[PDB]
Image (tube, coloured by chain):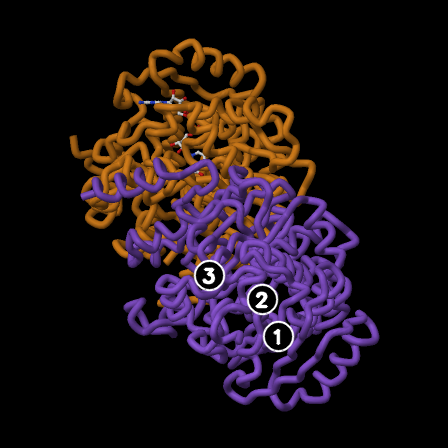
Chain colours: A purple, B orange
Amino acid sequence: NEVQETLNKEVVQTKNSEYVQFESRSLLSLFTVGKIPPVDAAALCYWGEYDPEMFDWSRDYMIENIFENLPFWTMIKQTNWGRIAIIALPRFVSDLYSNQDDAVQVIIEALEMAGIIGAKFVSLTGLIPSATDYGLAITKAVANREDLPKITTGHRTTGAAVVLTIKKICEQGGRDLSTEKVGFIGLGSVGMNVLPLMLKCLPHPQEITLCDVYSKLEFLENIEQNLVHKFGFKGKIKLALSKTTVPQEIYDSTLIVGATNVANVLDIMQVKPGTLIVDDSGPHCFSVEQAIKRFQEREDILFSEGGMLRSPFPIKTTVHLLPSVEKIMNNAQKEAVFNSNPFNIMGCAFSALLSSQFEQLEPTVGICDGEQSELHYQILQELEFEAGDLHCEHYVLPAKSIANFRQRFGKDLLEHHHHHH
Amino acid sequence: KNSEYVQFESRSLLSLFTVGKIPPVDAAALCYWGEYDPEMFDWSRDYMIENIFENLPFWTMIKQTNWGRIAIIALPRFVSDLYSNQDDAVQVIIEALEMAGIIGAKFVSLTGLIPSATDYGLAITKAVANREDLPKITTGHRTTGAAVVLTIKKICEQGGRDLSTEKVGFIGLGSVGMNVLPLMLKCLPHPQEITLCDVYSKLEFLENIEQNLVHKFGFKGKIKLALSKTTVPQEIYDSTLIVGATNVANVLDIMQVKPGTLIVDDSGPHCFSVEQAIKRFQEREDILFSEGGMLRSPFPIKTTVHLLPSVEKIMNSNPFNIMGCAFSALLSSQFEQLEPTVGICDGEQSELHYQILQELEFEAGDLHCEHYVLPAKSIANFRQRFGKDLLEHHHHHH
Ligand SMILES: NC(=O)C1=CN([C@@H]2O[C@H](COP(=O)(O)OP(=O)(O)OC[C@H]3O[C@@H](n4cnc5c(N)ncnc54)[C@H](O)[C@@H]3O)[C@@H](O)[C@H]2O)C=CC1
């Protein structure tokens, strides 16, 4: 009988706030009949990673019969500067690493759908750049086609969000960046945008530690030369180097900036009392659960996502869940959508909307021109954007706990703890 | 079995189009879900509209012909919903016209009883107003009329009977029928006798047709006027060829037509019982009866079929056949001489549809009725048993 389903659809509709709206019907269909206006940009995402027991299907069955090897338009972000479509590729993250040619093919199919619904630029979110030669494998295949929207890794806007987060975690921590020992764990695409931008827009730190794998020794040595001769960093520069896990010199840092794609390299239980942690990674370079545990028990650290932006005006999100997956889902999973901060938007996805509104913000393929992120940073300030409030995945750091941290590990107070004697 | 001309696709045609796996179409045709049957679905009528159809148009077929591509799009409505709420019917149609435009359709046919429920297109043209971003609509009734005349030609040919010595009875002279009668008198030998049958409300309308027959159409045979209260009057059963084009079903009793009668019926649903016509044919081979609006292409058509997945869980056409109404939209997109039709029209240009179909070597579909094809051997037996000289020598079961 059909009474439970019509009431369940009444619950999500009568709970649609002014800024979060579920829609049970296909966004693609609604767009084609004229009930959904076109978008100015889009962002591509994947279905995370497959649990054998989150879903009752096999991984191969999901790809073939649930996703049907087709991109799925799942969200719309309505902002004061345009509309962004969120399009899920019919793949998990491990599928994109094991077959790059297939990943490129399904991306191009999604680029064509993105053009139909109006997108002029398309962001590659998450680990998609890492698996597609940072966009280069896609650009080679699009060749001389001009019918498709232009791609972007968005990492210049992501780098701006990380520096905005560095600015915000220091303020809320009651600390000054010029007296921090900043450690960078992994200098990859985003890290190559954060480090130059940080030195141009924020006060220079007292000390900088560059940490990456052994293979990049001379690469870090030349980045060290960039610091002293291009950006004029006059402080101390240490070169940390690790295999599998961070070296024990990174725990001497008071601000840790993570930009690796390898998870759990940083032991959250070994950072000293008072450490600030900004990490743009999915998954994060530390155990989030142990970090929430340590923060709740001791109010010992400040830690946050680095790639999230906060809009000065709220954003209306329209959400269409995959119907066959919506049934297997529970009420607690749906609450995560309704309880999302309507001011927040990821820097990566937002970058595509920025390119469609400002022609001076050119799309990025490959890793290059870290300095250009300054233009992203300045425009985000002109629009009164800041970093997202301190949070990590599902967990928001309560203001009172942040206050307790600020009262005990602020400036002039860090030096009076045991591990800083 | 499995032919290369009928292919089932489990994935959404709309999605496949947006990722570039399906080329755009040149035209489209709008249909509906027949009539709600509680013995087929366990869902209630309103639940199907709200949660199975989701009040959205459904792109369900592609027909690839040698003269273009046609998309078949189902409105999220049953037939009686179109009559009971014309405003809502226009709104869903405009939504379908928007979808049809995205996938490239330049012209869109209104199939079935959609014209009869939308002022023959004028209820839609009013709502589209000055919008020029949408594909142009057509009732396609000039092409349907051409199909009916081609069927009249074929049924008399395969029956071994000459139309000039036939007594032709017209049941239902609405939009389609008014294209058939004049076109028949231009393309085929004039019959010996013509009977015009419609309801009492159209008495003077039929009387007006008689005067045009003798003064404009040049008909010199006998003209009889019959009125139908509910079922057809008993004087149409004196006709040897019956042409039907009504919007009400089972008005003609198939069991009362005389041995040797020819029946061409464009009505959908048919104005007679399909199951009894088949039963009478298999036991007696007494009649020829066929669809009237079905065209046969000289070259085969490749049909892609995407069934609505929720309905498919509960869920063999001739690859040369395509309905004249749907094909009319494709004709408008390839020959700007054939313009779309909205409202009841003069049907002067009806002959051009007939001539252009003949140049393309089109004819009517082989004699069939929905799922049932009349075997060629049985048609041969009919041809030998029911010539004009032999009709009086059969026992008419009274
Ligand atoms: N499937 C398709 O693609 C198409 C189907 N058709 C079918 O052709 C038929 C006629 O369609 P239209 O001409 O557009 O509709 P219409 O409503 O203009 O024609 C119906 C006519 O039949 C007459 N009629 C009603 N009850 C009668 C009775 N008991 N005895 C005699 N006459 C009676 C009416 O007065 C009217 O003139 C319908 O069944 C329709 O579904 C027509 C065109 C395309």
Query: Are tags 1 and 2 found on a single chain?
Result: yes
Of all chains, the one bearing label 3 is A
Task: Choose between B191 and B136: the one closer to the eye.
Answer: B136
Residue B148, horizontal then vertical, whole percent: 47, 37
> Label 1: how many residues lie within 10 Å, few (<14), some (14-19) or many (20+)?
many
Q: Earlier in the sequence, mark 3 or mark 1?
A: 1
> Label 2: how many residues lie within 10 Å, few (<14), some (14-19) or many (20+)?
many
Mark 3 or 2: in front is 3
At label 3, which amino acid type do we have?
Answer: Cys
Residue B239, horizontal then vertical, whole percent: 34, 28
Residue A184's label in the rendered image is: 1
Mark 3 or 1: in front is 1
Q: Residue at x 26, y 44 (%)?
A: A5
Residue A103, horizontal then vertical, whole percent: 56, 73
How many numbered circles does the render carry? Answer: 3
Q: Which residue is mark 2?
A: A107
At label 2, which amino acid type do we have?
Answer: Ile
